[PDB]
Image 1: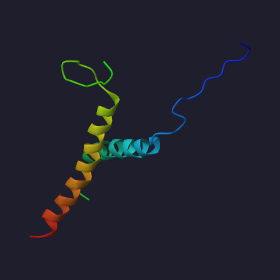
Image 2: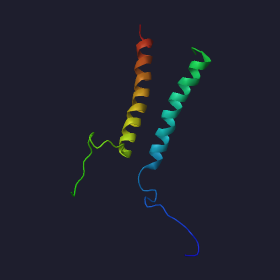
Image 3: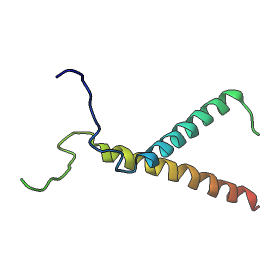
Image 4: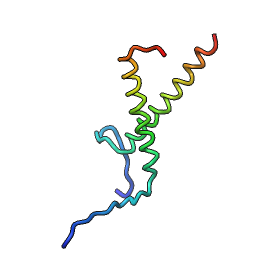
Length: 43
Length: 43
């Protein structure tokens, strides 16, 4: 009633860290290939 | 309906589906680079 505060139900139970790691991996893979193609470098 | 099922007719993007797609992406990216290197390594 006085202050407003919320809380997560999952409480960091499920493997969220695993998802994060994988997420960056995919984004990095594509992001790398994209920038690499623009650089026009074989090495 | 106690249990639940997912079908194409439903026409709805589930959360688990997103994980699956990404999963194969990462595995394919590495699996591809690995096989690619082996294809060049040997004449």
